[PDB]
Length: 402
Length: 75
Image 1 (cartoon, each protein chain N blue to C red):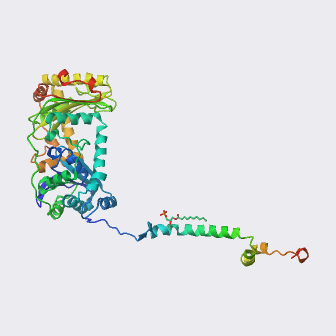
Image 2: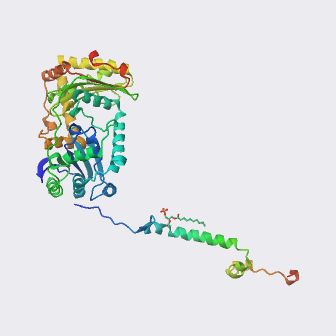
């Protein structure tokens, strides 16, 4: 991805040999920057609504003629708007993004009838998985605000048209916008962005209201639709070793009809439960989480104990074999993330919008058994453990039990 | 490079356009035949229908040329 600048907008493109191009606008407008709860989700859903030059209806009918597709999502850091089309149709897509950022008519009926109902279905689909809920709850406990804001719009706190219009006034500005073009000729994209995004406001960098503060605690989301448990450990100094530790501890199987050779995978033997360790770097803080879902609260409780033990055991000693297995699983995870268009866009988006240089999968550091065990030791000896239980919460573990 | 999709709006009225209607033109034809045959069948008994239309059809037309003998007709 050759990083450049076109009319004040950071543009990164990588040419390829495929008939398919992906163009993504990455906006610094994720939920950590959200003025009011849920506004970044609503703004994401308000992309490709009526603009002054082109109605939502006309856009969709013309997109069907190009056979293009549209993908949008919100993270804690970004809003990502991606289009996938044939290479030759690049100018149309650039101009479409320009219309969205410059000329969206944010109309009250779109919010009531189109945008908010779709945002609500989006969230309900995600929450069907109790593990999603548990990991969301864990961020809320760990960070409270900023990273602790909900990503998604909720019913209890309604977003108004004035909320969304104000946020868009901040976000849709040259200072908060990065363009990422996969299989796009880099010189051609710079020329097009340079003409189309010239009259976009300059604006100012959106910032998190307040510094990131870490907290421990418990969340007990009582649902009737499945059971899950997250054990998170907030990290004050995000370090790349936690990727290796996440992949080492593992949890999912690398093979059909198997349990797996990872410590966390082996904690689920004899139970219909699954586990996944994940590490979330947010630049200024991190979260190391272990999420366990299952149908039995008794089995979840059983696995949860084994999971925290596994982490303690790792803090004791890692073998050389296990450290190499961690390097391999971690390099692979890095590679596939840079391939997947959704995650790819945000990776270069972070490089462009912040200044965090991307770590190429081929440059992923190999951590010795000493470095891995040291990282696990810090986590086992955390002052601020977070536990989010979802489901039959009376039957799930508590932080002080773990 | 393509800047714009290439299309036109065809003339339309009450949700009909010429491409669509043209597909149904033959069907209106057959319905018209069906209505014609049916109508003619319904009035086959009317003497004027026989006199003016049916008796004039070649070969077949003699089916409708029938005379009552003057000996058998009170009127």
